Image 1 (cartoon, rainbow, N blue to C red):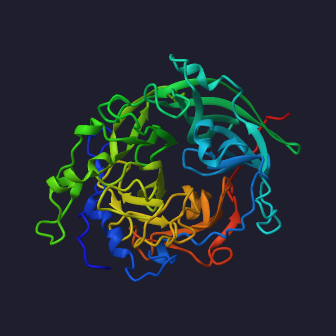
Image 2 (image 1 turned 180 degrees about the horizontal axis):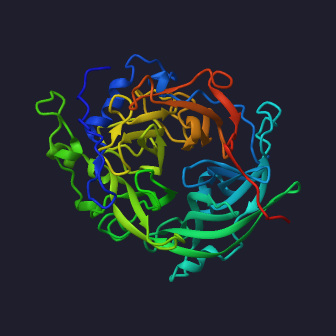
Length: 493
């Protein structure tokens, strides 16, 4: 540790889901990331501790769809405990996909949800190098996902990330972000975009032939930003609102909860941070003033993790609860939040970019983690209060560059992995954005090798460590999304 501020003291104390306690990931906490970085790290070398850095992905990577489509954010078939399922001998995944003819950076506004399947239980090394997935095509027929929007003049209409529950009778509830865009030919908004948390129900049919899906013809509009707990388009043209992950909390049986990315509901240009947001211990030599922070531009970075509760058993009606985590003046984006249960603890994992960090702060691309005694709690950021669980190899002493333009001095795996997702046994799956140096890089659009992150080193639930023995030198199978539970169903085709 370099000298710096102390981390904010977090109690981990549980609260009721309905309470409006909102844990803060503080500037104090986030500044621990800089303290863990090694100032002397030379050009293109990782400066972050190996134990919180994803193993380096080879630039010579296979493609999981044989280049049929761009693939990114991926999620398995789950139950209320986040166990991952095969059906009738097939592991099944949902992924954001886009036409491979698109420029990689243009794909976001043409995203759709597709699905892949592969035989379950094939010896991990008897499996093809690329994962052995079969692309099943698109989940939705043309025109289905548009049905929820009153305003049909949209220029673009996407399906963004979420989660998918499978029932014992083979029903699939697909929770996703249904998004409408209103853009001129140059990308400028005619009005703010319209992302909604949505549900679509279907069925899995699976044979020795493979897997097909039926249904997914009706979409229920579940949630949209309210303006009290979660920032709206009116409040912020480029507000975040997406990524439903649903689950059952062991401490609140028979009820269903959802976490999702949001922003703190403040007016963009008059937003302010307070002393809680900064979070310094009295008389820390490294303390900032509220005025200094408020004047820096840090107030433009006000991401949050939301929580909602299902009103019925069908999960077609939801009630907003107050945010469970705020990163005011810390980051714009806490993406793809998920709650992970282990050893009596609630782990909130979330994904962030380097570039979204507020002025005065810095951190790698990757997984940020938080632990508490309840789904609403005074969350403790993992690893010395920093919040870092699994960062891409990063030289934090040098600029980050961009995935379309890596920085001259940056580690070539700075953008090697994004939209990570923590599976049972701490196995982490993610997709490749960019690998390579400033003058020799490639884009991914395919999944990275799965890696292992051991959660709770010693008896300490606040620490994690990458397991570098897993697979080859830390890298497991390409696109490996293993099922730990298995279902057999009526459905066939």
